[PDB]
Length: 119
Length: 113
Length: 272
Ligand SMILES: [Zn+2]
Ligand SMILES: [Zn+2]
Image (cartoon, rainbow over the protein chains, first blue to last red):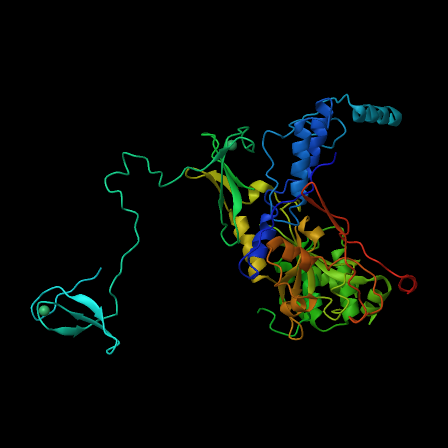
């Protein structure tokens, strides 16, 4: 079954826009903008823990991703938790400064095949 | 609940209404003196709940209820399930929106719905 | 105030862009001789020599010697392939970099306002390395009292002041018009220089009336949605439009709507 598509409650103001709160929203959009890290964390957690997309961690990541993609429509921050950070990246990434771990998933096999073909 | 003393004999006055005069008047029963009223106010009391005097400390009347607590929600900064939820208005928004406060003594994090 | 003359805006903008680039310093182009030479000349030749100087591989020390040794269509482009020259600006916490009149695809807002092609300027807020601003540079968290409360940094106030007062480049002052959905994810915003003919408020009210929307994000989204690249077609009045009812189904206590943005078109409309 698919996940629920019900979004957050809309925020309605009691007064008209005075061109200041829109600037506040535009500046605050940079803060707590975790749209790009949720997908990376989900991929890392799927590659690490077997039986991926079955545990509650993947469901929480998907819900957070939906809430973050709803940020541009409704003013609801994603609120990315600290404990869900990957702190580890597979070989098929450009994060050379970050620690690299050898992945044994299907993506790891594909990357090894590509490396062997190029070499 | 107001009271005043007529300048003639310095005695309490009771309010009364006259159909012909169509105005508020005060006259005491001690002397036949009638004076004009001011502000047309005969009763003014601030509503208070101080009825059970010297009894609200022994028996818990529960004047200020405690906020409910839930364990279904999960905090973000810490992995604690207990949190306090309540409804309150925003700074400029309309309606009631749900809030959450973490119950972890070492977390101190609050977030909206 | 140093110039105090009728110097054009395009040449001044090009000079500012060249100074911002690591080609010529500030005082090397602020002398009287350079502006005296650049004041009265041919405009096309002046633009050609300015862009040639901007194309110099290394840093130029003497601009006067270089410039001594060196010596309509917009509407058609918009109608053909929507080709416009839009100014792009980069605002950093330290300074501001002007890229220059880079060619880019034109949007709908410049179709009916093609005479102010130079008043439109794209402003992007980046870091010193022209990268995205980190979350620690804006509203750093601090534990004050029983609960944690974010504390706004000076960069936050600087961005607010830039958005409010606006950016002044020569004899112009750019004002905030709107930002598209893609620009919100790229920290970009459109700015239009107010003129005696049409101001920013005039364009804003010409696009539509946004006072009906009571949501902060929804109002911005609706104001910025009409900035995508598109091809101009014929004009249709408001006399022949239908009001077909839609279909809704409510199962398991959930509102599921089949028709979200679906529509209906004819064959003659497709041919036209
Ligand atoms: Zn009396
Ligand atoms: Zn907590």
